[PDB]
Image (cartoon, rainbow, N blue to C red):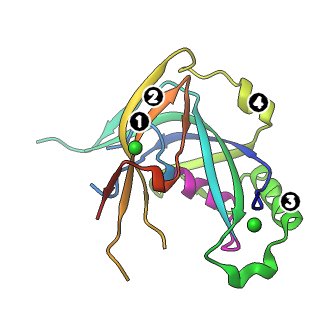
Amino acid sequence: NLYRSRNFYARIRGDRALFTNPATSSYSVPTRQALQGIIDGIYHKPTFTNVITEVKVVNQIQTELHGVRAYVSYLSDVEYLVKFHFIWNENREDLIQDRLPKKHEAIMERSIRKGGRRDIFLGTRECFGLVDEISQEEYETIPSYYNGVTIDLGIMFHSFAYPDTPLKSYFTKTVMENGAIKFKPQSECEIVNT
Ligand SMILES: [Cl-]
Ligand SMILES: [Cl-]
């Protein structure tokens, strides 16, 4: 098959988060867009594309209100386990000389381990996230509050089209099975808006 990095696993924690529908209060769980932003914050170069395949929602979904009434609903006390990998960016063949698997996998590993190359945000400039590396064994065994049930989380924003033409948004039916949410390719999203 085409080049694919090893699977990487990251744990993301935050006291507060705000995951929104930018093509319209927080969704109850991260969107693919939000997770993409988190993982890219750990390490990204246009040579490669980070591909988020699954997230585990570890803690009970809780929100809290902030604002005035004559309004902002944030998630509270969140923990996500993210499974992802990278592939070479087909849209940047001009960077083909930098497609060095050992180099990028080493940097990714180091980057997750140190908590990311950049500050990690969970939806606002005040919602900081904390990233650390977990093993596949840990990804598989850390208990989720939602283990035992499967829950329809409804239609959620997936991502914007990429990469002139009007901006298209993709949305997806979102099911959380024993705390785990898988992310389908943009091309499989049932709902598209321009
Ligand atoms: Cl390839
Ligand atoms: Cl869908």
Q: Amino acid under label 1?
A: Ser
Tell me the amino acid under the disc marked 3.
Ala
* Percent position of residue 32, x then y: 50, 50
Mark 3 and mark 1: span between their CA atoms? 33 Å
Q: What stretch is highlighted in magenta?
A: 33-47
**162 magenta-colored:** no
Image label count: 4
Looking at marks 3 and 1 on the same chain, the residue that comes earlier in the sequence is marked by 1
Q: Distance between the residues labelled 3 and 4?
A: 20 Å
Q: Is residue 69 above or below residue 48?
A: above
Residue in front for this viewpoint, 190 or 52 = 190
Picture disc at residue 106: 3
Badge 3 or badge 4: first in the primary sequence: 3
**Above or below, comparing residue 169 to residue 53 in the picture:** below
Left or right for 115, reference 194: right
Mark linked to residue 138: 4
Quarter occupied by the N terminus? bottom right
**N-terminal of the two: label 4 or label 1?**
1
Residue annotated with mark 2: 61
Q: Where is residue 86 in the image (x, y as percent from the top left)?
A: 71, 58
Residues marked 3 and 1 touching at CB (< 8 Å): no
Whether residues under marks 1 and 2 lie with C-beta atoms below 8 angstroms apart, the answer is yes
99 to the left or right of 73: right
